[PDB]
Length: 221
Image (cartoon, rainbow, N blue to C red; front, top):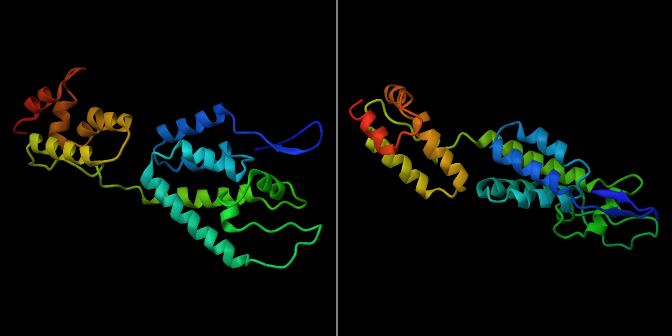
């Protein structure tokens, strides 16, 4: 964010690696929970647009979510521009050119410009404005969740467990997800999503049941 020199200038300080590591941990752990939003807001306190983009690049592997954020950001930026039309005239020595939507998203603006806007009297709070757009995006992401690409693969009441396993793994293989997410899918979701009768059998197996043991256990259930 922004800090003052002993020589009095407002200068930029990169987000701490510990704040960044915390944010990446929140996303890893709190998948798409409403809980992500309040955390994002706490962790991004004081952030310039550059800092906010830094936080997002850190969780960019979530491509479907990043795509949703992009569309929200483009939409809000477009409305900002409608409300804040470009004015071609000269800028008075005591005025400051207003930011465009892309300046707020950090795309067409420099850190120096972001800081100049943020610390003006009164501010042009481009960090807070961009943060609101991101939050609009995050809310849309959580609200949409209720996915189908794995989560809605459920064993049928009369489905042979070997067929369910096949469907599950086929769906799994076609996804673009990190390995740690896929590991949770194979080790816990598969049982989680088995039918009532198979799940009860599966949950009564030992600590280290192999998938072949699982299929043996649930055969004709």
